[PDB]
Amino acid sequence: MKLSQDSSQIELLKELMDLQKDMVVMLLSMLEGNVVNGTIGKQMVDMLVESSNNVEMILKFFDMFLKLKDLTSSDTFKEYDPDGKGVISKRDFHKA
Image (cartoon, rainbow, N blue to C red; front, side, top):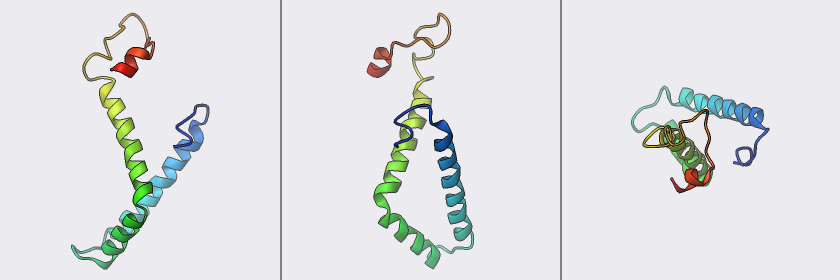
């Protein structure tokens, strides 16, 4: 969140994303030998419910960015100002 709130710092955000990807890969490797009522699955869901707020913020961040990608090319934003490259006064962007 702190890194997305500003620019000129994309590298740190990308490295943090790679670290989170490796962490969830570790979780998947822990789960890859589970049963429907596995003790490891119970431990993981307990860890999630303990870290409820953090994973909520991560999911909200991902929702925001995925919905932005879906909305920038959904109804009228791709042909709003089709003169040259992307020219948005950001006021129409906010209202849309």
